[PDB]
Every structure is written in C-alpha cells, then in structure tokens.
Length: 113
Image 1 (cartoon, rainbow, N blue to C red):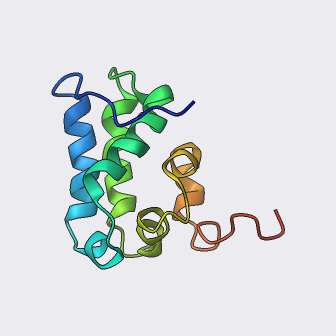
Image 2 (tube, rainbow, N blue to C red):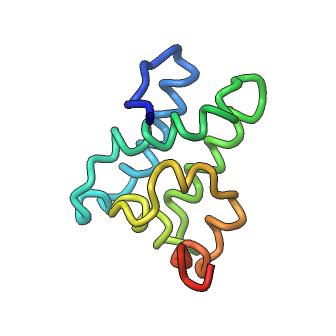
C-alpha cells in the first residue's frame, strides 16, 4: 500500500512541505505542464519523510538542498521529469542528490540499466 498526502503535523513539517511547493511555484513551469504543485510536494514529502522526517538535523538541511535542485538553472529538466510524472515522487525521493544533479541520470531510467 502507498500513503495519501499526510496531515500538517506541526509548523516544522507543514513548512517543509510548503517550501517544496514554493520551489515549484517560484516559476510557472508546473502551469505549462498542467501539474498542481501543492499535492506533488506532499507526495515526495511522505516518501522522503520515512528516513529524513526526524526533525533533529537532516530534515532542516535536506529540504533547503531539495528546493535548490527544484529551481536550479544547471539542471532545469530535473523538475520537468517530476511534474510530468516521468520520475515518480517515490523514485525521486530515494534517488541521491548526486544522481538528481546529473543531467544524464535524470533521463537514464531503464536505458542499459
């Protein structure tokens, strides 16, 4: 079974979720693709929350680094794959920041894998 978009919890988790939304809303890219960003953020959020959701240290830093990759000019196609459903919230969350940054690997899913 997969989990639906979760409750706000507290001003930590809801803030992290809305800042991932704001990384998608800072540009009208999601409007051109026709994907609603506010649900997409929460789907990725619950997938990454399983490891990172402990609000002690990594949950604070990982969200900031994630926002950067969602609005980045050196890899602008990364958001394109997520918004169009080419890479699912589950797969992009368990993918490392190194592989997300690589322009080759965000288009290599099952190619020679």
